[PDB]
């Protein structure tokens, strides 16, 4: 289990990150709700506290080192330790190679790849002190390559290399570093779409059904578990088989 | 997700898998070659309160395997979970590899698990629920003086993923747990100290480590995870190309 | 004055490989099941000026393979290059797969090439030079309704890498060319446009494409490239997890 | 072959990049020597033309978009086309996670990952018009993960994802996108070592020998060849087998 562990989930004020935080809190963890959206932070913190959960809001642009350090300080002041870090905050600017602005590239790299580097760096020293840590990075099936997704594929593939490098380096300190690569997941974007969009993608799913945020939360609960200390350096797809062939 | 068959349950990993699954209320069927060891295991598990049956069988021929499966289905009426623990294989340099060493490795290492999957997957797709977990090890990636083991284990990679895709629509998942180095209490302390140094987490794996990953893949809620090659290795798999 | 054995040379891919190596001055030995096809191919290659011998054989048993190998080494005195072109295998949904379908796929797809490697690899290590190129295809990764093919082809992944590491010190390399979709002039035109649409370069592969990759790996200068799984696929392998 | 193809090799004023340019020119190609070291560009350009090769020097920081665009414009003015691009320019800032400055990260990413993105973007439109291109990216065995190499492993892993993404996207235009991951290669650093170190590393090489710069040049010659138009999206290791197990 993860009873009495402290979990920092970046970008967890909405979407699957929030659902991962909820399920973590329900399984006995103190959760830090993070987002760059300070109002989404407060709303989720309020929601969780009402549900009886041990929760702290930590507003910070995880792409900014100073903001990241303040988040980690706020977490340590509050809970005294950081047992689990889920680098869930991410974003994408996509487009044909010729249409990608330098800014489309810089930001996708900054949030997904550097942000994951900044949070992992700022947190790991505390896990070293406690001789226990779980770092799980959220990548994507798109690290395998997606047309029109040069920045996203580059960034999330970089997250895969970081996962492998740090799994090797931090293992001796009792820290595991793993990566979850979600395929296609039922999201608010999805519910705000027109039918014809939906029916093409579903047709590309081996299960014929969409994955749900709980599928991600449940997979992350496994990797974060106290019992999963011998699992590290892994890239685990939550795709319903789509990652086996995405053509 | 109430009934599970553990093939080659008569070793320390099979025991640990049985304990984890029984711990979650799963009814168990334990297949293996060593009836003595199998019965002692069933006795212990029943003694703790688990529903369990044993089936002695050292078979690799398809017909005998289908029979074993039928026994289980006779008792429980369904197989929700298939865990194929690997059988021991002799790793040897190429010159020491004989014509029969090749055939045996393929039969016990690859053909046998295939036959189990053929006997169980149709049932699972028909019932609309299935969790298949193949237990392999790092030799499938290929190391010096393991060619006959590597050829057999390596076949499970494409096999599991092929059937994962073939069965996906019917609520079945097929995944692989790849064991790294597991402590055994018959390994010399000197080969433990040497092996642990080469593992990033600086410890050997335990059978419980393996069962924990098997239990995750077999859970009712792991319905969107299929075709996966999950290493339980302490990080040693990060040293291999093509493990991701 | 380099010598190469092409197993299953009796198809369009085998022809193209033979032509590429002959173009580089390699002395050729062609093994295959269709002696008629082999003789015609050797006739054409001799007609163009190549040093070539043919050896008919539809074998999957080790002894017969070791003999075929003996014929070649009698003529040339050494085998510097072994290219194992894959033999055709029928992919079918799981229900249509019989007990003998499993054994046959393994025999020709995995056991037979293994036997060729056992008969040739030791010689190469003794002479201090060797280039082994296994030709597989995308089904080794596992697709729906290919389980019997995938199990056999997938075994070559660990097998090739195992012997690559085992032979590295003695100047031998073992690599794999994985074929994508290759045009064959018996596919329906509607399946050419259908397949080509799903390939990033928007065309089917040619036998020459495959031979170009085989010729690179077999070149004298590729002495530091070993254990590789090189896809010649027009980009279609980029849609698979675990192809890198 | 590659006779009379135009090849732009980033970071080719010294090291492996330099030697790839020489071998490319010897096989009939027009080569653009690029580096940030303007004196090494001049000396190498001097060396090459003296050998009778068609060569152009293009000093530019590959991490700067404007410098890259000026490089490509100079190349197009000179040779009218760019058939081959080798993203060989690279560097590394390494160290334990806690010891990595924010600048150690930013530069490794900028040169290796963004730089490869900038050159690929600026060149690809010319290959689209010519319906022919070969893009080859230099990654590293360390994309699989290396202790103390978080930035390098992250950056080069990102290059692998970019390779896959653009192989998918640019294929219809006659452009292949591949990646070479060099293992251990005899470099000037190598000679700067003591025997006791050297003999440890070699012993971890399956062949027992070092790779040489020609090993990369020859593999690059294969991927760039006119005949290799159906090879794309690949990561080809030039490691003597060390990439099969680097533990
Ligand atoms: N089907 C999918 O949604 C899918 C598929 C593959 C991968 N992923 C990845 O999963 C993760 C989350 O999925 P999602 O659907 O919720 O995407 P999302 O757009 O909803 O982003 C998740 C949260 O991250 C926050 N965020 C963005 N930038 C931030 C920053 N600099 N600092 C702090 N917070 C920031 C956002 O406010 C947002 O609430 C992402 O990393 C995404 O790349 C999602
Ligand atoms: N044994 C090895 O050296 C080895 C091993 C694995 C990978 N690699 C990679 O292969 C490539 C070449 O290897 P190398 O040893 O010759 O590296 P190197 O640093 O010695 O040479 C690369 C050249 O690129 C130049 N350059 C051009 N633009 C630059 C820019 N914007 N920023 C920084 N530098 C710029 C550098 O001045 C340098 O001269 C690198 O990408 C390296 O990461 C090398």
Image (cartoon, coloured by chain):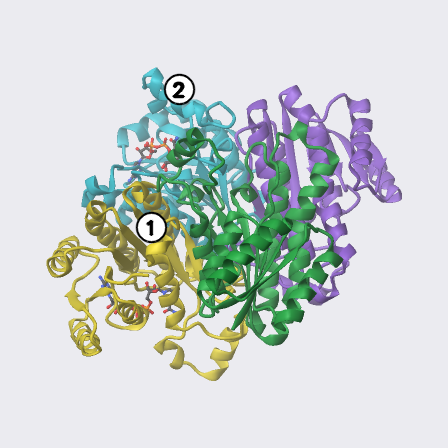
Chain colours: A cyan, B purple, C green, D yellow
Q: Residues within 10 Å of mark 2 (few under 14, many from 20)?
A: few
Which x, y percent locates residue C143? 54, 36
Which x, y percent locates residue C72? 64, 66
Q: Residues within 10 Å of mark 1 (few under 14, many from 20)?
A: many
Q: Are marks 1 and 2 in contact (CB under 8 Å)?
A: no
User: Which residue extends farthest bottom?
Assistant: D195
Q: Quadrant of residue B44?
A: top right
For residue A152, side relative to residue A181 (left or right): left
Q: Quadrant of residue B197?
A: bottom right
- Ligand 2 lies in quarter: bottom left
Q: Check the image and report above or below for B211 versus D197.
A: above
For residue A193, side relative to residue B235 (left or right): left
Q: Nearer the viewer, residue D105 or C101?
A: C101
- What chain does mark 2 sit on? A
Cβ(mark 2) to ligand 1 < 8 Å? no
Which x, y percent locates residue D174? 29, 46
Q: Which residue is mark 2?
A: A199
Residue A193 shows up from this direction: yes
Q: Which residue is rendered at x = 46% and y = 31% of the image?
A: C188
Which x, y percent locates residue B191? 69, 65
Residue B137 shows up from this direction: no
Q: Name the mark on residue D177.
A: 1
Q: Check the image and report above or below for C101 versus B122.
A: below
Q: CA distance from mark 1 to mark 2?
A: 31 Å
Quadrant of image for the N terminus of chain D: bottom left
Q: Nearer the viewer, residue A67 or A79?
A: A67
Q: Check the image and report above or below for A88 versus C4.
A: above
Q: Which residue is rendered at x = 76% and y = 60% of the image?
A: B98
Q: Which residue is rendered at x = 24% and y = 42% of the image?
A: A97
* SS under mark 1: strand
User: Which residue extends farthest top?
Assistant: A195
Q: In this rendering, which labeled residue sits more in front, label 1 or label 2?
A: 1
């Amino acid at each position: 289990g993860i009873q009495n562990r402290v979990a920092l989930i970046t970008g967890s004020a909405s979407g699957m990150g929030k659902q991962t935080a909820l399920r973590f809190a329900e399984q006995g963890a103190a959760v830090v709700i993070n987002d760059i959206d300070a109002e989404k932070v407060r709303a989720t913190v309020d929601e969780f506290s009402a549900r009886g959960h041990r929760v702290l809001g930590a507003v910070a642009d995880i792409g900014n080192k100073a903001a990241v350090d303040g988040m980690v300080k706020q977490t340590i002041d509050a809970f005294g330790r950081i047992d689990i870090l889920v680098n869930n905050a991410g974003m994408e600017r996509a487009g044909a190679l010729r249409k990608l602005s330098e800014a489309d590239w810089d930001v996708t790299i900054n949030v997904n790849l550097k942000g994951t580097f900044l949070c992992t760096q700022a947190v790991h020293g505390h896990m070293v002190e406690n001789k226990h840590g779980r770092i799980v990075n959220i990548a994507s099936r798109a690290w395998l390559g997606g047309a029109g997704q040069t920045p996203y594929s580059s960034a999330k593939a970089g997250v895969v290399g970081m996962t492998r490098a740090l799994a090797i380096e931090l293992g001796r300190a009792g820290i595991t570093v793993n990566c979850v690569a979600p395929g296609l997941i039922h999201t608010p974007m999805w519910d705000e779409l027109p039918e014809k969009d939906q029916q093409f993608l579903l047709s590309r799913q081996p299960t014929g059904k969409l994955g749900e945020p709980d599928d991600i939360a449940n997979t992350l609960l496994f990797l974060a578990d106290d019992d999963s200390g011998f699992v590290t350096g892994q890239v685990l797809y939550v795709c319903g088989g789509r990652s086996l062939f995405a053509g | 997700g109430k009934v599970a068959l553990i093939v080659n349950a008569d070793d320390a990993v099979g025991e640990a898998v049985a304990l984890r699954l029984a711990g979650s209320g799963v009814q168990l069927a334990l297949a293996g070659a060593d009836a003595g060891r199998l019965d002692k295991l069933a006795s212990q598990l029943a003694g703790k309160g688990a529903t369990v049956m044993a089936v002695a069988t050292a078979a690799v021929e398809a017909g005998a395997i289908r029979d074993s499966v039928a026994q289980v289905k006779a008792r429980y009426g369904r197989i929700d979970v298939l865990v194929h623990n690997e059988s021991a294989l002799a790793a040897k340099p190429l010159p020491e590899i004989s014509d029969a060493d090749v055939g045996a490795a393929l039969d016990t290492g690859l053909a046998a698990p295939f036959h189990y999957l053929r006997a169980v997957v149709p049932g699972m797709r028909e019932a609309g629920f299935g969790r298949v977990v193949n237990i392999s090890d790092l030799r499938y990636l290929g190391l010096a003086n393991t060619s006959s083991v590597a050829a057999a284990r390596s076949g499970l990679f494409g096999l599991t993923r092929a059937l994962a895709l073939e069965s996906a629509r019917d609520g079945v998942t097929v995944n692989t747990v790849v064991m790294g180095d597991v402590d055994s209490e018959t390994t010399p302390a000197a080969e433990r100290e040497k092996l642990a140094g080469g593992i990033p987490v600086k410890r050997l794996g335990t059978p419980a480590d393996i069962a924990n990953a098997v239990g995750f893949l077999a859970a009712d809620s792991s319905k969107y995870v299929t075709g996966q090659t999950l290493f339980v290795c302490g990080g040693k798999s990060a040293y291999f190309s093509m493990s991701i």
